Image 1 (cartoon, rainbow, N blue to C red):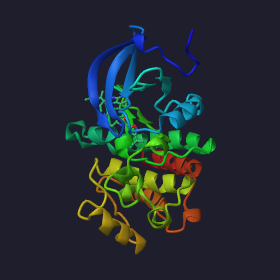
Image 2: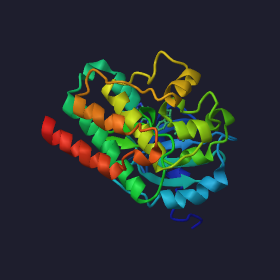
Image 3: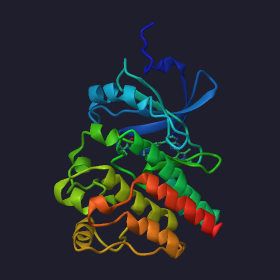
Image 4: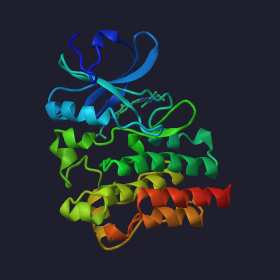
Amino acid sequence: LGYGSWEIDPKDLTFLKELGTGQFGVVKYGKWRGQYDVAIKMIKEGSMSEDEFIEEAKVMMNLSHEKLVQLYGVCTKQRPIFIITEYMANGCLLNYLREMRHRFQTQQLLEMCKDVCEAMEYLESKQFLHRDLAARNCLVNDQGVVKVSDFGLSRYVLDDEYTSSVGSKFPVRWSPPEVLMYSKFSSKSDIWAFGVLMWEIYSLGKMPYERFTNSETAEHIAQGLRLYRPHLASEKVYTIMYSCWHEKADERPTFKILLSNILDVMDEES
Ligand SMILES: Cc1nn(C(C)C)c(C)c1-c1nc2c(-c3ccc4c(c3)CCCC[C@H]4NC(=O)c3nc(C(C)(C)C)no3)ccnc2[nH]1
């Protein structure tokens, strides 16, 4: 009584560990009904357009793919509201990449790219944009599988420093020229970001354009210059990520085409 299909009873949650603090505040690890691992976003007051998100959560619930971090439900009766998601034991892809001890083989790096590409192909098939695809917004489970996280939530951020294209928190380094110039988001801006994500993976989580500021990056990419080949990327892998950065959005591949290209390179580089 008093819960829709989207609604989780917060009394069913056991809080176990703090995972960190992001754009909407603290996120914790816990259990649901004593036995199911979950992550719990405790949505900071003022940080989210909550009513709009709650309506969208109904759509997000139905986005189900193995390589997408699942939304399990929301707790909306109380302030702060909670968002309950799939838990990922190996944490953020960016941090995971930066842990040199893993000493990833290039086949593992390509598999990470494929994991993300599968998730993104699924989202593309639902005409659903991520809008902030980057290694920091991917997660890794205890089997080393990478999944895409927090797809679509950018739409509900109430922080001008995140939303404004000249804001301090805006993902300049993952954005195509038409986003930077006209804030024109499309499937093809997710494609561009995916190419940068591939670059992050093969660079083991270096900052894209690490020697530039955001402002200098915007200027660089408007002049047609690009990231260049990470040491661990083969020429074939580099060709794939580079294909994501065509100046003309309509000349960039789809995620289906990228997936096919990644599978081909796996077959050629096994
Ligand atoms: C990390 C981490 N380390 N470890 C070990 C290895 C030490 C573990 C187990 C984790 C871990 N973390 C998660 C999370 C999670 C997701 C998002 C976030 C957080 C945590 C908090 C950190 C800040 C970003 C934070 N962004 C957000 O909440 C958000 N960003 C957005 C954007 C795009 C801005 C729209 N929307 O929500 C979810 C599911 N399983 C997890 N496992």
